[PDB]
Structure formats: C-alpha cells, structure tokens
Amino acid sequence: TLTYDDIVGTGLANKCPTLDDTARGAYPIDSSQTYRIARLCLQPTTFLVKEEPKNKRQEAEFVPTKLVTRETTSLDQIQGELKVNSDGSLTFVEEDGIDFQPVTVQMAGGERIPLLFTVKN
Amino acid sequence: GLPWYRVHTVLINDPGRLIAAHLMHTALVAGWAGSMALYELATFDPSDPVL
Ligand code: CLA
Ligand code: CLA
Ligand code: CLA
Ligand code: CLA
Ligand SMILES: CC1=C(/C=C/C(C)=C/C=C/C(C)=C/C=C/C=C(C)/C=C/C=C(C)/C=C/C2=C(C)CCCC2(C)C)C(C)(C)CCC1
Ligand SMILES: CCCCCCCS[C@@H]1O[C@H](CO)[C@@H](O)[C@H](O)[C@H]1O
C-alpha cells in the first residue's frame, strides 16, 4: 500500500495492478443487478509490427520492435457499463478513461512506427 | 636532385623513416576499410536477402 512518493520515478506508475497466485475464484453474476467496470488497466509488454514484404505470397509476419518513448504506454482509469445480456454473456461498454497512448516503436534497421495505442469506444 | 619517380628512395638507408612510411601506408589502408564500410552501411538496404 504505497504513496506517490514511494512510486515517483520507479516505473511502477506505468504498471497495472496484479493479483496473487491464489486469486483463482469466481465472481458471481446476479442477473438482476446492474454492474460496472470501475477500473480497467492495460499494460503492453510487447509491440509487434507486421512486415511488408515485396511480393504478396509468403505471409508477412509480425516482428518485435524497440520502444523509444519510455514508460508512457499504459491505458488506465478506464470505466463503463458491464451489461448482462439475454444469453448470460457480459458486454463491457467503455465510457471514459485514459484510453489511448501515443507510442513510437522502432523496427530493426531504424524505421520508426508511431501508433495511437488505444481501446477508445 | 632526385627525379620524381625516385623520391621515396630517401628511405632506403633510414629504417626509422621507412617504418614511419609503412605505418602511414597502414593508416591509409585501415582508414579506407573503415570509410568503405561506413559508406556501404549508409547505402545498404538490409530488407531483402532473397532478391
Ligand atoms: C610494395 C610494392 C612496392 C613498393 C614499396 C615500391 C617502392 C619503390 N619503387 Mg617499385 N613498383 C611496384 C611496387 C612497389 N614499388 C609495382 C607494382 C611496379 C609496376 C607498376 C613498380 C614499378 C617501379 C618502377 C618502374 C620504379 C619503381 C621505383 C620504386 C622506388 C621509388 C618509388 C617512388 O619514389 O615513387 C614516387 C611515385 C610518385 C611520386 C607518384 C606515383 C603515382 C602513381 C603512378 C599513380 C597513383 C598511385 C596510387 C596512389 C596507387 C594506390 C596503390 C594501390 C592501388 C596499389 C621505391 C623503392 C623507382 C625506382 O626504382 O627508384 C630507384 C622506379 O623507377 N617501381
Ligand atoms: C602512402 C602514401 C605515401 C607516404 C607514406 C609518402 C611518404 C613520403 N613521401 Mg611521397 N607521395 C605519395 C604518397 C606517399 N608518400 C603520392 C601519392 C605522391 C604523388 C603526389 C607522392 C609524391 C612525393 C614527393 C614529390 C615527395 C614525397 C616525399 C615523401 C616523404 C616526405 C613527405 C612528403 O613530402 O610527401 C609529399 C606527398 C604528399 C603530401 C602526397 C599528396 C596527397 C595526395 C595528392 C592526396 C590528397 C589527400 C587528400 C586528404 C584526399 C583527396 C581526396 C579527393 C576526393 C579530392 C615521405 C617519405 C618527399 C621527399 O622525401 O622526397 C625525397 C618529396 O619531395 N612524396
Ligand atoms: C618481437 C619483436 C618484433 C615484433 C613483435 C615485430 C612486429 C612487427 N614488425 Mg618487426 N622488426 C623487429 C622485431 C619485431 N617486429 C626487429 C628486431 C627489427 C629490426 C629493427 C624489425 C624491423 C621491422 C621493420 C623495418 C618493419 C617491421 C614491421 C612489423 C609489423 C608488421 C605488421 C603490421 O604493421 O601490422 C599492423 C599493425 C597492427 C595491427 C598493430 C599491432 C600493435 C602494435 C605492435 C603495438 C605497438 C606498441 C609497441 C610497444 C611498439 C613497438 C612495436 C615493435 C616491437 C614492433 C609488426 C607489428 C613493419 C611495420 O611496422 O609496418 C607498419 C615494418 O616496416 N619490423
Ligand atoms: C597487397 C595490397 C597492396 C600493396 C602491395 C600496395 C602497394 C603500394 N601502395 Mg597501397 N593500398 C592498398 C593495398 C596495397 N598497396 C589498399 C587496400 C589501399 C586503400 C585504397 C591502398 C592505398 C594506397 C595509397 C593512397 C597509396 C598507396 C601507395 C602504395 C605504393 C607505395 C610504395 C611506392 O612508393 O610505390 C610507388 C608507386 C608505384 C610503383 C606505382 C603503383 C601503381 C599501381 C599498382 C597502379 C596504379 C594505376 C593507375 C596508373 C593509377 C590511376 C588512378 C586514377 C584513375 C585515380 C605501393 C605500390 C602509395 C603510392 O603509390 O605512392 C606514390 C600511395 O599514395 N596505397
Ligand atoms: C587521428 C586520430 C583519430 C582519427 C582518425 C581518423 C578520423 C581517420 C580517418 C581516416 C580515413 C577516413 C582514411 C581514408 C583513406 C582512404 C584512402 C587511402 C583511399 C584511397 C583511394 C584510392 C587509392 C583509389 C584509387 C582508385 C581510384 C581513385 C579510381 C579507380 C581506380 C583506383 C581503385 C586505383 C582518433 C580520433 C581515432 C584517435 C587517434 C587520433
Ligand atoms: C562509427 C559508426 C557509428 C555510426 C553508427 C550509425 C548507427 S548504426 C546504423 O543505423 C541505422 C538506423 O538505425 C541503420 O539503418 C543502419 O543500417 C546502421 O548501419
């Protein structure tokens, strides 16, 4: 249970919360209640970019890249409705939050690939 | 004086300056190799070893 001052500059602020190995339970859904996701967090650990080879024939592969914009990549504080559908499926409908990060990664050889890493809407 | 095509003969009796002239030749050749590689790296397209 840490304060800002414990965290500032460690890199921990770009990390999503985790759960212990013991958290293998079950969260009951009461078809009668209304639900929300009060916090969604997404922390990327890998960016892959599909190569664009010279002849379409040979499937192009996603290859690893180097992040050049530092620990600024996570999506967080995202919230919204968690609907219970006729068939008992749940539907998350994002309303708001820090739901995008610009990110630049670099291909082998140096080509930079900016992207708007997002789950908007 | 020495004709133009004999100027380097001043080194024949001078082991120290011969070694200096050799070192310089060696400096030029290693410098070539270095420069040649950088020019190749600045122009080489590594994106297709097939075609
Ligand atoms: C390791 C190889 C080597 C070395 C160390 C020498 C060294 C020497 N040579 Mg010999 N020679 C060689 C190979 C070599 N030669 C080869 C391959 C040939 C046939 C092409 C000759 C034909 C030759 C003749 C006919 C004579 C010599 C002479 C000499 C002496 C004076 C050179 C001088 O003052 O030139 C001064 C040269 C200049 C001021 C300008 C030369 C410019 C050249 C022609 C063009 C530009 C060259 C360019 C920078 C080359 C890059 C080199 C690389 C591609 C190989 C000196 C002892 C002379 C001698 O015996 O003196 C008593 C003499 O008359 N050489
Ligand atoms: C490996 C190359 C090399 C080395 C180690 C030597 C070493 C020596 N030379 Mg020789 N020489 C060379 C090549 C070399 N020379 C070439 C290519 C020429 C024809 C220009 C000569 C013509 C020459 C003369 C006429 C004399 C010597 C003499 C001598 C001695 C004294 C230094 C001097 O006066 O240089 C003078 C030579 C130069 C300064 C070479 C000029 C440089 C050329 C033009 C290239 C320019 C370099 C530049 C950075 C790149 C251009 C790039 C381009 C895209 C524009 C010493 C033994 C002197 C002496 O001892 O005689 C008894 C003397 O009088 N040299
Ligand atoms: C153990 C004794 C010893 C060793 C290790 C060498 C080794 C060498 N000699 Mg020889 N030489 C020797 C005895 C020795 N020599 C004696 C007793 C004589 C009579 C005086 C000669 C006369 C002689 C002449 C006239 C020449 C050589 C040259 C060379 C060099 C040719 C290759 C070169 O330039 O590669 C490329 C070089 C490298 C990759 C760098 C190597 C790292 C160096 C050695 C470290 C330098 C620091 C060290 C403290 C300086 C002293 C070095 C000296 C012992 C060679 C090479 C370094 C030639 C030369 O120097 O051309 C440039 C040359 O012209 N030698
Ligand atoms: C085994 C490999 C090898 C050998 C044996 C040599 C040997 C030689 N080099 Mg070195 N050289 C090498 C590799 C080698 N080189 C490499 C890899 C580089 C980097 C490109 C060089 C760069 C270099 C430079 C910059 C110089 C030398 C010079 C020399 C000569 C110095 C001794 C001399 O006075 O000759 C006297 C000269 C001769 C006997 C005439 C050699 C004629 C050659 C073989 C043909 C030249 C073709 C044509 C006439 C020139 C047109 C060029 C023009 C279109 C630009 C000698 C012939 C120096 C020299 O020639 O000083 C005058 C000189 O300046 N070399
Ligand atoms: C000093 C110093 C330094 C630096 C160095 C450098 C930077 C160098 C460079 C160098 C270089 C950069 C060099 C170069 C060289 C080159 C050469 C030597 C060339 C030659 C050429 C030729 C010889 C040619 C011929 C021909 C022609 C022209 C045409 C065709 C035919 C033929 C091929 C014949 C350092 C910092 C490290 C440290 C220590 C000190
Ligand atoms: C003395 C050599 C120092 C210079 C090194 C230049 C960086 S290395 C250089 O980087 C480029 C882009 O990342 C690549 O396209 C290229 O293939 C590579 O050679």
Image (cartoon, coloured by chain):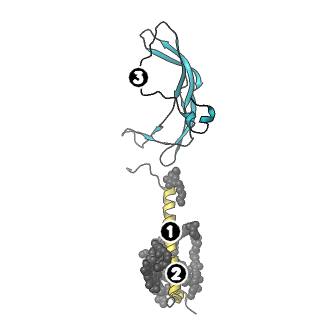
Amino acid type, mark 2: Ala
Dot 1 corresponds to which residue? Answer: B32
Give the labeled residue for mark 3.
A24
Element on which disc 2 rests: helix
Would residue A94 be visible to someone looking at this image? no
Residue flagged by tag 1: what amino acid is it?
A: Trp
Report the residue that reaches farthest toward the front: A1
Q: With respect to residue A53, does B28 lie above or below?
A: below
Give the chain coloured cyan. A
Count the numbered circles shown.
3
Host chain of mark 1:
B
Q: Respond yes or no on whether mark 2 lies under 8 Å from ligand 2.
A: yes
Between residue A50 and residue B6, name the one nearer to us.
A50
Mark 2 is surrounded, within 10 Å at the Cα level, by few (under 14), some (14 to 19) or many (20 or more) other residues, namely some
In the picture, the disc for residue B21 is: 2
Percent of width and height locating residue A13: 57, 34
Q: Is mark 1 within 8 Å of ligand 4?
A: yes
Q: How far from the left and from the top, in percent, is residue A24?
A: 41, 22
Q: Which chain is mark 3 on?
A: A
In the picture provided, is B50 more to the left or to the right than A36? left
